[PDB]
Amino acid sequence: GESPQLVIFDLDGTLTDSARGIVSSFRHALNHIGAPVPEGDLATHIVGPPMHETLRAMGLGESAEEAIVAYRADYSARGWAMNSLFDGIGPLLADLRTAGVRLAVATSKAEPTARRILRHFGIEQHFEVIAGASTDGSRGSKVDVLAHALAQLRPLPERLVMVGDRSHDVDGAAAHGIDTVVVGWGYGRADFIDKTSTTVVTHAATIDELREALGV
Image (tube, rainbow, N blue to C red; front, side, top):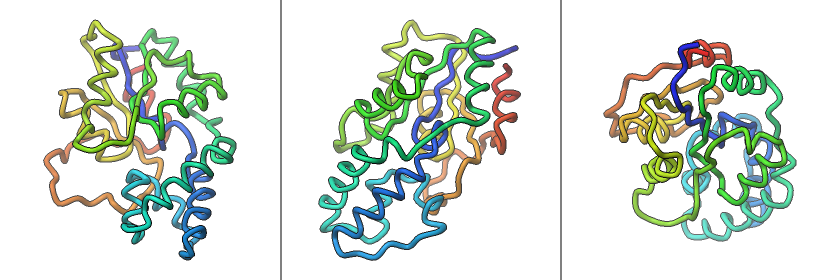
């Protein structure tokens, strides 16, 4: 297969069904502050934007910090067991490995937690570098994720590509000059932005579109 040298995958929504786990803690967080919780389409509608901003988009601004820590605690308590990945992704990772391409990830709910989760599933060592979120800070650390990951996996290979689902990964990869392919795993709400510089990007509906796009 005419695969690249390294493929950076998303680890939040493209790698696992975080929806189940997130909805669990999401319900707890809002209920903890006396706020209601809409069920149903909220599962997919919370997939896409960062939980911090998603919660802020749900109306939380003042007691947002309280709900955030509640979400984190509940997610760290039960959210880890409310996830899975057995589907086309499994054989995909195997086939990609067969082609001789190096795989890595640059997106995380929390790096320490990601280390645990990926270790639990047993796909941790199947990736070269696991990165995404070292700490929740300020400024535009949107590029540093991929940037720092690359400096770790150095030297830098000729062919690099990202696989995501959101404008966050497509913009970051393009910011460093790395091509990317977005999938159609979910359907969020914060899809439409005002500042859209990057309009062109390949879209993979099913898992088979990924393999052929990557060239495995």
